[PDB]
Length: 238
Image 1: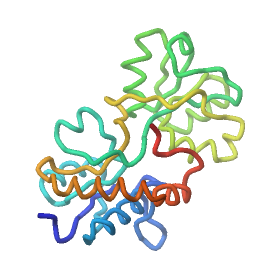
Image 2 (image 1 turned 45 degrees about the horizontal axis):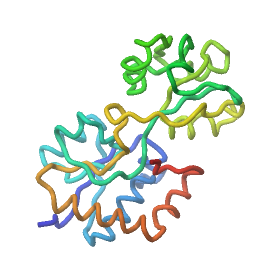
Image 3 (image 1 turned 180 degrees about the vertical axis):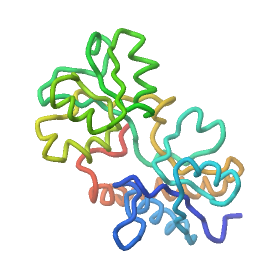
């Protein structure tokens, strides 16, 4: 059976997907999608704030029933839990100076200095696929020094999460003269084939209901109107 109330864990530190406004209400595209889906499933849903590292543990322990927290559908993720159909893409993308010919390819990146934040999935991606093929991958302890170095010319480009750099630098005045160089980088093992509602593998009726609500609010234009409230591009992706 479907739960009486679906408890949804989210990490409220990740606008524009999941954050808390100044009055403390949950806000973002993850919330709107969750709320819309739950409305279509006709079930009560309750948002449970949780540190991101504790989301999958809370789910396996049944302290929560779903995860909606830009949780990438990576290969390792799927060994432990199940996912709904994709909610939106969370790929990475290179940033360089406006007019840069740089592409996210080996023949383009050979011998170039690409910055990445240490500990990120972008650093893992760039170290396992780019550093070992003659790309100079530079790890940074501090995200704002990446941007500063890039503006200074000590990097040819930076590998960032696409939405985060969209919101955090490119829309800011400091990034006016910078832009994405080439298309978003896709890698199922590092970035998932999107994000999805994270669910326990036993919870097939819950998965079915989220997927049906998801296809439906897409097919009738609700997804696009809702995304337009936050995004200028195709957040859903491929």
